[PDB]
Image (cartoon, rainbow, N blue to C red; front, side):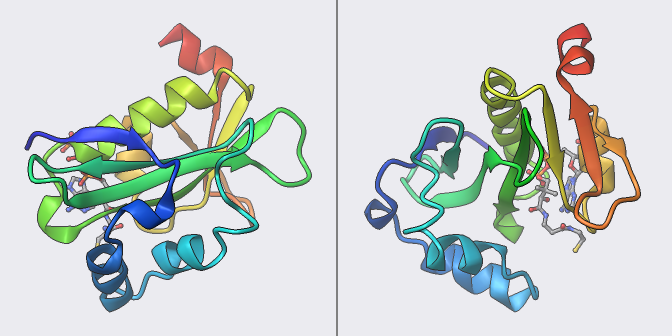
Length: 147
Ligand SMILES: CC(C)(COP(=O)(O)OP(=O)(O)OC[C@H]1O[C@@H](n2cnc3c(N)ncnc32)[C@H](O)[C@@H]1OP(=O)(O)O)[C@@H](O)C(=O)NCCC(=O)NCCS
């Protein structure tokens, strides 16, 4: 499934309702939280970015990004990763994550994330599963580089 991955510079330039609706149906708040909190966590500052995957017809099929992990130094947190159900299993999440990781490791020496649902996906990308309160997966830059 052909997509383009694009940096979000203007949240108001996309129709987010499909992503909001499907994610909410599934019990996920992550798209809602992202869009509601977008004035404070804009993903526009240095060390942060939000991406969308656009279909060949300009429709949003996924989102995901990164920003600074609070309290840690040199650690970034991967945030708000979600692919529309009908768009899953076509390589979109992998393309999105590869872009995020390659860019985020320019700023951070470690990337972390919290995912209860997608361990196989994240392990396939090289993340290590960890038992923390705030994080489920971690990846050091040196491990990323060595791959
Ligand atoms: C996890 C997620 C981001 C992966 O993105 P994706 O575009 O579907 O994944 P890709 O097609 O790039 O596949 C990469 C890996 O992701 C995983 N994956 C594939 N389809 C998936 C799906 N429908 N749901 C969860 N994970 C999936 C597989 O481990 C896959 O490895 P493989 O290609 O070697 O078999 C995406 O499916 C998603 O947002 N799922 C949300 C719902 C969820 O968490 N699923 C749990 C069960 S309800």
